[PDB]
Image (cartoon, rainbow, N blue to C red; front, side):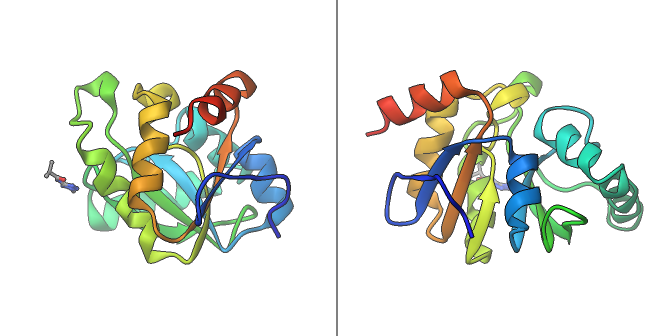
Length: 165
Ligand SMILES: CC(C)C(=O)Nc1nnn(C)n1
């Protein structure tokens, strides 16, 4: 199962890891994607997860959007995990760089509660523009299921652990 994680709370764990590499190693039941409403997996975690699936995630996602329309900011959908996981939970955190309401970050993390265990990135962090320290705080105060957080950046990982209240 998951190895090398630092335990933050009863149910939240954290590791300085590449979530693609982590997913290929563990093959978790659920890998969380830092998705946008259109499921256009261009950059950040989404671009990296999609590239690891050889674009199969994007092909599946375009069919999902053609049938269902876009997700809501704060919403999610469950699609295939391809070669990374059994399932991919595509969760849309607010993109602060698009002027989206940061208050939707709690709604976004609530989607994790539908899954007993997940491998995930910090929602709205990275290219989504939110403060990752705030994202981790909302994660630990919202998610009640077992979440294994993969933080790519070592310097950010150290800052998150050292500042964790
Ligand atoms: C109270 C408001 C800001 C809120 O949480 N709205 C919401 N959360 N997820 N979706 C979708 N819509």
